[PDB]
């Protein structure tokens, strides 16, 4: 029976355990170029046969909504990534690049020529939320511009190019960021998508864009090198269950048509504890609803399932042992615990993470200077 520390065949790739580095935007890729800081950060977190997913990576100049996040749409960026990927591979890691377009979750300061961010809609994220600016202040999300159909195809092409570039850099594959209210989610979620054309209305129409992206990148680099991340549960849908199942149905159908499986489906879940980790005491209620959603979605998807969001050591063990997921990703714990895999294997204490340096730009401080367990001198 599978455990969290058991080997796994993720289609093309042999993994030695089920602990995954979740994608984590950290803003250390100064002027969008992966650098020596990123090399050491991913190297520190690499294990033999361990799966790593990079921070969200720009597919185009309009795809940014954070400062000093890496791109993979220029040769200079590809060359920077090669150094990261080579180091991870030297440690025996398998590593995927997350392809990220933020859509309306941006600001004029992030956009070429100060243009409006692009989206499904003209409606902005409400003033309830604010955006981190390059000068360490917080700003207001602006009104986005709704894409025309031909422009949506231009973005699909940007994903295709980014995937090709990822493989050129040596990445084992890519993950489509279709979660957390960013561009593709702005089309999926009926709370955001108020379009009246062929990209709006039906679940079929709302899933069109993300399916076109999956189709294009699969054609470019192979189904077995493509993972997809979603989060159906200011980005809400009136029926998260049906939305998740709608995406899953279309992925299953595409796999059956093309004759092979995608690398995986990756789904995040919300939590209801004070610190966002773990389970509430035996008898919230929204937690059981969400728990059931995750099992329903996994059950419906034909292939590898990665769960993420508030997983503890115990909940990760249970998810794999009970068959709820094949792989378990960890985000915040991996910020502060470079050797998180070893710490989980030993049930060792976990370093506290410092949220104040999640998105600062120092190559060392709060980035590569969290300690591993003392290995001593053999
Ligand atoms: C600082 C930070 C950066 C993140 N960056 C990304 C990202 O670039 N792409 C993404 O899909 N999720 C991102 N996430 C969400 C995480 O991947 C993860 O789903 C979330 O932190 C919940 O998992 P956890 O409880 O293990 O932290 C980020 C989260 C944090 C805290
Ligand atoms: O707390 C979060 C959750 C998701 C995120 C994402 O999808 C991209 C960048 C930063 C993020 C921060």
Image (cartoon, rainbow, N blue to C red):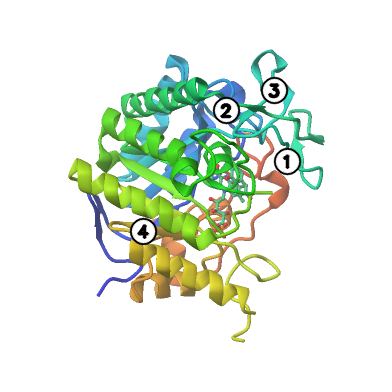
Q: Nearer the viewer, mark 4 or mark 3?
A: 3
Q: Residue furthest left?
A: 259
- Confirm whether residue 101 shows in the render: yes
Disc 1 residue lies near ligand 2 with CB under 8 A:
no
Q: Classify residue 141 by image quadrant.
A: top right
Q: Earlier in the sequence, mark 1 or mark 2?
A: 2
**Position in image of residue 223 (x %, y %):** 26, 40
For disc 4, the neighbor class at 10 Å (few under 14, some 14 to 19, many from 20) is many
Q: To which residue does mark 4 refer?
A: 305
**Position in image of residue 247 (x %, y %):** 41, 50
Q: Report how far apart the C-alphas of labels 4 and 1 lie in the structure.
A: 30 Å
Residue at the location (60% across, 58% down)? 238
Q: Classify residue 127 by image quadrant.
A: top right
Quick check: marks 1 and 3 in contact, CB under 8 Å? no
Q: Report how far apart the C-alphas of labels 4 and 3 lie in the structure.
A: 36 Å
Q: To which residue does mark 2 refer?
A: 63
Residue at the location (49% across, 46% down)? 202
Q: Report how far apart the C-alphas of labels 1 and 3 lie in the structure.
A: 13 Å
- Confirm whether residue 98 shows in the render: no
Q: Residue furthest top?
A: 113
**Position in image of residue 29 (x %, y %):** 57, 29
Number of the label disc, if any, that sits on residue 125: 1
Q: To which residue does mark 3 refer?
A: 116
Q: Earlier in the sequence, mark 4 or mark 3?
A: 3
């Amino acid at each position: 029976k599978p455990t969290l520390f058991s080997a796994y065949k993720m289609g093309k790739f042999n993994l030695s355990h089920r602990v995954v580095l979740a994608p984590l935007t950290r803003c250390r890729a100064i002027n969008a170029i992966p650098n020596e800081a990123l090399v050491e950060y991913y190297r520190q977190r690499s294990t033999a046969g361990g799966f790593l997913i990079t921070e969200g990576t720009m597919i185009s100049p309009s795809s940014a909504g954070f400062p000093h996040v890496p791109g993979i749409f220029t040769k200079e960026q590809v060359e920077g990534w090669k150094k990261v990927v080579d180091a991870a591979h030297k440690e025996g890691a398998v590593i995927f690049c997350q392809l990220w377009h933020v859509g309306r979750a941006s600001h004029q300061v992030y956009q070429p020529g100060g243009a409006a961010p692009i989206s499904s809609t003209s409606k902005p994220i409400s003033k309830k939320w604010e955006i981190l600016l390059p000068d360490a202040t917080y700003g207001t999300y602006p009104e986005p511009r709704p894409l025309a159909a031909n422009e949506i195809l231009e973005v699909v092409e940007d994903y295709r190019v980014a995937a090709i570039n990822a493989i050129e850099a040596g990445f084992d594959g890519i993950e489509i960021h279709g979660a957390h209210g960013y561009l593709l989610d702005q089309f999926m979620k009926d709370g955001i998508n108020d379009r009246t054309d062929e990209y709006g209305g039906s679940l079929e129409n709302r899933c069109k864009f993300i399916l076109q992206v999956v189709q294009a990148v699969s054609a470019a680099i192979g189904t077995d090198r493509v993972g997809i991340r979603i989060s159906p549960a200011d980005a809400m849908d009136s029926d998260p269950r049906s939305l998740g199942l709608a995406v899953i149905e279309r992925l299953n159908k595409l796999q059956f048509k093309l004759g092979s499986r995608l690398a995986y489906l990756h789904v995040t879940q919300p939590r209801y504890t004070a610190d966002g980790h773990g389970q509430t005491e035996a008898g919230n209620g929204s937690e059981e609803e969400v728990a059931q959603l995750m099992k329903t979605w996994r059950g419906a998807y034909v292939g590898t399932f990665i769960c993420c969001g508030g997983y503890t050591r115990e909940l990760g063990l249970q998810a794999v042992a009970q068959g709820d997921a094949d792989l378990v990703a960890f985000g915040r714990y991996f910020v502060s615990n470079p050797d998180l895999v070893l710490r989980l294997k030993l049930n060792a204490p976990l370093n506290r993470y410092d949220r104040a340096t999640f998105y600062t730009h120092d190559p060392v401080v709060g980035y590569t200077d969290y300690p591993s367990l003392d290995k001593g001198s053999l």
